[PDB]
Amino acid sequence: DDNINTLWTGVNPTEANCQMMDSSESNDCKLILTLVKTGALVTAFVYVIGVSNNFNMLTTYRNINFTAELFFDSAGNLLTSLSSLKTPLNHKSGQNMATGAITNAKSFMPSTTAYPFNNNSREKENYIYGTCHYTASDHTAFPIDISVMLNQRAIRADTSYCIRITWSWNTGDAPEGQTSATTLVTSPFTFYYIREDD
Amino acid sequence: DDNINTLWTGVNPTEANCQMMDSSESNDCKLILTLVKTGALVTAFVYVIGVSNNFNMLTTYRNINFTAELFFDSAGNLLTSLSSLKTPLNHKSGQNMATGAITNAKSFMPSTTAYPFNNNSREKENYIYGTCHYTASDHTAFPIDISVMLNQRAIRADTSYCIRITWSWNTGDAPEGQTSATTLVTSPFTFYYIREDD
Amino acid sequence: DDNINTLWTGVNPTEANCQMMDSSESNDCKLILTLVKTGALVTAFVYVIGVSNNFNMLTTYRNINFTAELFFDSAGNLLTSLSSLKTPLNHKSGQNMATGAITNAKSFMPSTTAYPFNNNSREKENYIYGTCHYTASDHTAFPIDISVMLNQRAIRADTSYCIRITWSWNTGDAPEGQTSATTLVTSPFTFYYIREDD
Image (cartoon, rainbow over all chains, first blue to last red):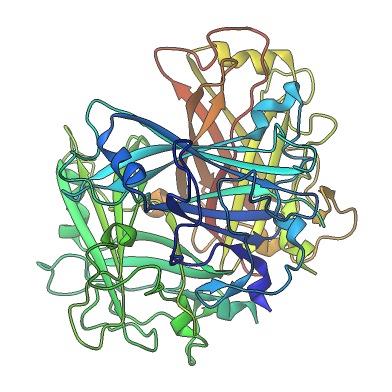
């Protein structure tokens, strides 16, 4: 069954599954996250589809950053209370998540050997960088910086694995104006990391 | 069989398999396209090797764009009449294409759930961006912009899936002078998308 | 056995496994390289963790390039005497290298059909480009250019496959401008190439 090689959020969930902004008091966007087992690595495929007005209106600002913090327990299961993503991940079932148990969830996690916790000497190894784009109302591509930090620092005793994905930009002109903003959508960002063993 | 997880053009086809320019009277380049099933995703690996002098001479201009439009039917089979690529894709057979029937061709296609057709409010989700490089005669790397649009709009009724790939550059100087232009080759660009189910 | 789809260095080797710089008294860094078979392609995942003080202090200079030269024999075995990486690759065994025979080592190699040797007219096809980042002591990300040349030129009769990975920067400011005591860590760079057949 190839479906168990994927751990994901499903494609375009009906309702917002993620509370990205600190100012938000409920889910403000759809986090689309797909983790695929690819040999010793995980192929991580991530983007956001904005839902709340305040999140969508971030496209009108010149200086923005927002972070999806994903915390997982020792079994590789998402801790929804601590995490930005409020719906657990599961396997592929068509375009949706499966509903059963998760096979080898821990082996989707970022390796604590490759990406340690509380190790100042190896702190640089926890960082992955890249770019994605916001497609503007005029069809131009607005580049957005992405920083991923794997593990490095835990926030609670039961947080065994961490993925923190930060989207940011600092420009002279905002992606949109107040009247042109619609939905904050980031283009998919694919990154790779050495996966934990079961 | 691992070979059926690849749907591709084969390596460096003897003859030009693609008509990139409308002004060309026949195939003017080799489109190298490899689609690999990677869990819930497809790994899409693409570049061009120019063949015709007119296409190759595009490297002598400062402002250029060209697009490979790939249209597929409901079975996931290439519609060569509509598409830039004039030879159907098939599975891996060594460095070449297999000649038999394609297994699960529909699941190589970009998801219509992830990448809808004619949906204005979700149109931003259809776009993927990146960069490749042209290796110049002096061995400097000339960056080329890439815009990919999946599905979004279908030009004919039997078209069920679309992959449109646009290479472009707009610079102060052309990649090559008149006496240094040889072959327009783009470095491989790899992108990812959520695949359709069978 | 999925473990045989990876050919790698293992995670964070105890000792430096690579001599990046010709002048170094011994191995000067940890080359972390993971090659994963992905359909017709190899997903190549590479970065460097500096070990020696002389190599780590390269980040204080403004115009630096260094290259990992990886040479393999006709069976796909690393030729350590000729190569920057001085420890053979092997399969995944947890976070470490396996210690047995390598299964189908040849099909991890860059295709000589896709990436020829001594063919000037096709030389542009041998190149892959990208960027990674050096994380500075202030935790800012400094972009580093990466160039990969596959095959193209052999250095000895038994060198059947070559992977040459060059990290470089040439900017107004050095990657590290705040201290002489910080580890040269490059963020992971992932590239793709068409693999040889067994």
